[PDB]
Structure formats: structure tokens, C-alpha cells
Image 1 (tube, each protein chain N blue to C red):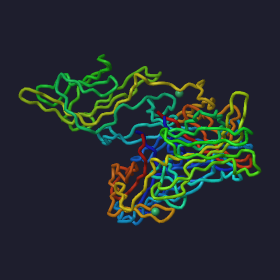
Image 2: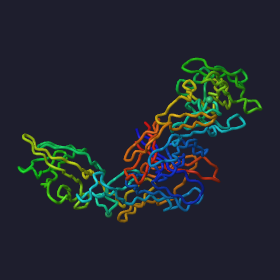
Image 3: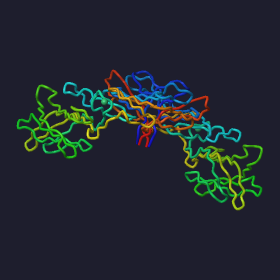
Image 4: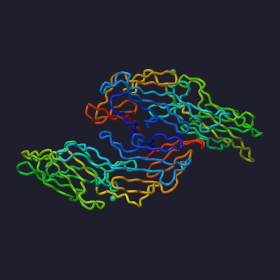
Length: 274
Length: 274
Ligand SMILES: [N+]
Ligand SMILES: [N+]
């Protein structure tokens, strides 16, 4: 394990950390986007009152790596969750999340009958190309099991026709959840081989999606509030910034508090990772 | 390996990072001390001119963990060097450094004839206690070899009499180098056993001490300047903040530069560790 620290706080005033002052928080440089804050308020000496320690994360959006709004590739939602990146499976709800497997703009060729492994048990197969070489029949699988299939027409006027979005139901009680996007550039119909050329892939590990429950507790951050696109997690009871010590906030986040006299206070937050 | 990022820089103006804005730099919370800065100056578009990229580290001082100025335990020198802590072996010179092995205020008892292993091949032995139980004969060793010895009187008026400082010569061309401090609280003369009680230990790995040479080069930071207590390391040639990329500065430090149009510039430094 290793440690990533934030800016140092001094004195007994209110304090605030975000991505710019705490390198542990998630941050996307291309879109210049982050989601997390940690605040300390209303200290009495070194004791934070109930509700004075607040971790907040609010959904934000970033450009697909394969950026092409006209073909249906504009932005997707992102959310920091205890210093890790997650994808909200419904872009308006902060409490249902999954890990991103792929966000890619690399070119791949799939030959009919062959599988492109996407990672974590997910794959796409070109099952067939049509005689005229303008349509490809794709199939999406998880651990060898059928999930979905679609016929994609690759040389129409409409650039969105090249994109396949897999929408699944009953994922953490959400329906119409986009779990995979695949953009097919073209099809190549050779003498012996036909191949599909892919460029643009986005996949979340929907099979491992989770829900943050109102009853969940994260160490001393044990008052979870879910308000649409924002999680706000707060302390139910007093929290002491014990001098000359480390104190868990929760779920891998900590404060380091300096060895000073009780007339002073100096501390910074940090995150522990592996 | 893992990554620790600093604050984001935007635009074509001059920029500066220190410990408060770059969590990769060394920082001591108890003494509130750091030593490192990284600056970017005089950009022409995304090209830093010769001398425009400067890494500086200046020796600072911290309290011994066993803090007791009267017994000779006040402060020792520290220096960040490419995000790692080093001890300058001469507190006025930034170019001769060693790693800290121990900075301790824990109590230990050593029985006569027994060895306290200090780490990294170093040990101290209580060889004998005197009949009156007011003096202990200590010996310092490295990989079993004799380095130094001293008779310490533990119940005099002078509190500095309890401290043994080992001073060695010919370490990276420095003489009178304090490599070990040992503070003996007291001696206990039992019926069968006599033991020495230690509290206060400080050790640097002097055997692996190194010198930063004027001719040394650290990737693209290849102009080393040594000025007493300060190392200033600079770029001899142009350095491009290539957009949508990572670029090595040197010795584990990098810039991450955002994918933007050439009308903009956004980047942050980071350090790679293992
Ligand atoms: N919800
Ligand atoms: N020097």
C-alpha cells in the first residue's frame, strides 16, 4: 500500500478539499473534471461536531475517447467514489455504479467467426457479413453466454447507424442501461475472408454493478444521503483530530494530525491504496 | 508502480509547484517543513526555453523524534531529492546525502554482551557496565565489523553526558560526520544481569552515502548547479509540453499534458514510485 496526501490545514477554522487540493480525488485532465469534496466545519478545539465532516461526490461528464457526437459518441457520466473512478449506470443517479472496462478509439479488425475479447469476460463477435458487404451481424457475450446481438448497416447516410448501443434491463433496478457501445467503421469482403473494422468501444462491467444504500456506513462517515446525482456522506457523531496521530475517516481515507501543543492544530487528509 | 499528481496548470503563463501544491514532494507535518520546488517560466507556446524548467531543493531542519536540546537532541537536516527524503551528511551541503535508517524515541534495554540491531547491518552493543552501575561501555558495529566505541557516564550533572555521537571521517570527502546518536537513560545492575536502557536513537546509512556531481544528469534536467545548501537543476535545451501526452522531466518525475487544441495548454506534474 501507498499514501497520497492533500493540502495541509492549519488552525481551528473551516476547511475544504477538492481535486485541485487533494491528489487522491479522481480527476480527468482532458475534460478538466472532478467530482469529490471533503469539508471540515464548526470545530470546537480539535473536535468536529456531528455533520461537520462531509464527503460529497456529484456526477460529472466526460467526452468518450472515441469522440464523435454525430455517430452518437458525445459524453458519458463519471463519479469519484472514495478516490476511485466509477460510472453511474444511470447518469442522473449517484447511487448505482459500475467500473469502466473500456473507453477506446483504437482500430480493430474482427474476422467473421472470431471474437474480440474486451476484458473481464466480455467479448464481441462478428457472426456474419452480408453478401453486399454493407451490413455486419454482431454478437455481445459475457463468459461465453449470449447477452445481445444486432445487425449494423455501415454505409448508410446516417452516421449513428454505425453505432451499436447495448441496452440492458434489471441492472440494480435500472432499465435501458447502456452497457456497451460499438462503432463499426466499415466491412471488408475479401476473396476468402470478410472482416469488420471497429473503432470506438465503451464498456462497463455491468455484471458487477452495485448500489450505495441509504443504510450503508463508511467507517466514521456513516450518514449516507442520496439526492439524485449527489452522494453526501457525513459523520453521525463527534470526530476528534487526535494530535500526533492518524485517524480513519473511512473507506481508505484518513487524516494525519501533527504533533503540536493543544494551542495549535495542523492536519492533512490522505488516501491509502494498493 | 503508482502515480502522485500535483496541481493543474493552465495557460501559457509562468507556473510554480511546492510541497503544498505537489503531494509528490517531501513534507514533514510535525515541523511543517519541505524543501522542493519545480517551476516553469517563459513559455513560447508549449515550448519551455533553456533554463525555463527548474527543480530546486534547499536543505531544511526538523526536530529529532527524541527531542531534548539540553542532552544534545535539537534538530537535524533534511532534504527532498526527486520526491524522496535524504539526510545531508554535512548540514550546509546539498550535494552529499544518505538515507535515514532510524529517528526514534522508543525505550530499549540492552543486556551486556547482547546486540540491538538498528537495521541495515548496523548494531550497538553494551559491552560492559561498571561495578558502580554509573557507566556503560558501548560499541557500534556494521556487518559485524567494529566502527566505534565509547564510555558513557549516565548519572552526571550534564545531560549531554548521556548522549553518544559517532563522528566518522572520509565519508564522501567529509570529516566529523555524525552518523549515529545514542542516548542512554540509565543502567540497571541486577544480581545476575546488568542492562543499559536506551531512549533516543538516530542513524544514517553512511556506508551508502552518495555525492551529487556537477556533471550528473537527471533525464531532461541535465544542468546541475550546487550552491552550498541548495541544488538547482535546470534544462539545457528546449522542453516541449507535447499535448495529449506524458513527458519525462527526469528521475521519476513527469508532466501529464491534456488533449486540447493548440490554443490552450493544461498540464500537471507527477511522480512515479514503486
Ligand atoms: N436512487
Ligand atoms: N559541495
